[PDB]
Image (cartoon, rainbow over all chains, first blue to last red):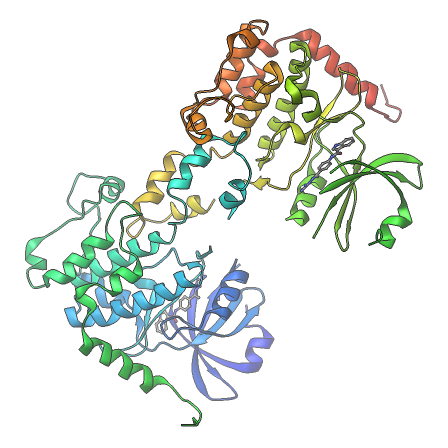
Length: 281
Length: 281
Ligand SMILES: C/C(=N\NC(=N)N)c1ccc(NC(=O)c2c[nH]c3ccccc23)cc1
Ligand SMILES: C/C(=N\NC(=N)N)c1ccc(NC(=O)c2c[nH]c3ccccc23)cc1
């Protein structure tokens, strides 16, 4: 098939960047590069979520076409997926993991403050701004995300007719956001060590049993070169009890992220990317 | 304020039947009585749910007006709420409880087969067709109801990044419908005995603690006149484990409901209410 006419009106389509499919395109009016995500036939509400979110580590949408397929136009992240930096046991310098992880926490903290849970945080969904190692990252793919009440309404009446499982669930409600902090923990683990913590490689313990017990695969030799603070943070994110698990605020206050050099590097990358109008004093 | 013009066009409004508010009205075209529920400002989707459901023990919607307030036009249930038959420790003959309860089970079975959970089953929400003791009942008020998938999508990938609480919840998912069977249990308890099983009258045990332990208030003297089969069914519905609790199918197969006299009386009331066109053989 062809591209829809309304898209072609505004953009010149070019090469595939990844595969769902992401394409390079050029905005006709500006002659600037953009990325165009094609989702074949809540994409509707992924759009609404992304329209309303405004954070430098969250992907922004420039345009949207609902045709034979869906076309989502985004700013181009030249660096590609974080995934490609961690396959084949490739490993990032610890300093680079911190820079990237700080940005992911800031992103996910912003989501949670704004009532959004992502639910599919993984290396595939973290984009890099450039091929340089020090860069901005942006979180993408809000197709599984959830907007954070039915329990609350039930509890305003007397529970004369209310089932016991509803009352038992009051203990744990309101912690759905913690699934994102677990995923972040897993991502940090992979970045620091170049391998996944839960996996069916070697071992007879099922993947499910590894995850629900929280018994991650620790290989000392791979970790010897990783600092203790780093691994400590990983341990506080991979807590099995969602109520005890570190939140993004607690992670941002952890010793490993009290690194004014890394923060400076982040601030420097931010202002480098920004094109502001004049300011009064 | 006044009634909206589009309503007045079709109906002549009359007296209050109950209080939210329910009014007697007359359809101009037929000169027949109807009931009009006024909900002041998912009423939208309560309408869609009710439009698509077709069961003789579920209230049918005749019309709907979305104005200053919402107006829902329904068939008139002259008998009023089941609530009024059980306040002040009034008690229904056991035979009448069975007739009514059979109808409630049939209704709720129909909902569950069609992917609908009611979530607010109570005497207030069961309507009687007439002031006669043997009558049809209809379940109403689908304002808290839910249409029965996010878990299922999560489980089609590998759970490398998936939080342990999601995997633990696979054990219990798909049993939300059981909240309706608990409520039915509580309603049957009230109907048979004229008092509620969980209540803050006398006792120092909190309502919550009574419900989650399943320790209903049993007063032998009130129950002596109730059959053992009846109480047995109540016990199988007020099971605290939602997976072990009786479903509507299991309740319909219980000895207490194997009563061909009651069933005949129900069939007789059905055909009495129906106005069918001629039939070929
Ligand atoms: C919103 C979204 N998905 N939503 C959904 N699936 N429901 C989405 C997914 C991937 C990209 N990828 C990219 O920009 C790139 C991925 N690999 C790349 C390599 C080079 C440049 C850009 C990308 C951008 C947006
Ligand atoms: C659909 C609904 N509510 N939905 C919602 N609240 N979201 C509804 C609630 C109550 C009635 N009541 C009745 O028909 C009567 C209640 N008491 C009566 C006494 C005499 C005759 C009729 C009724 C009918 C419909």
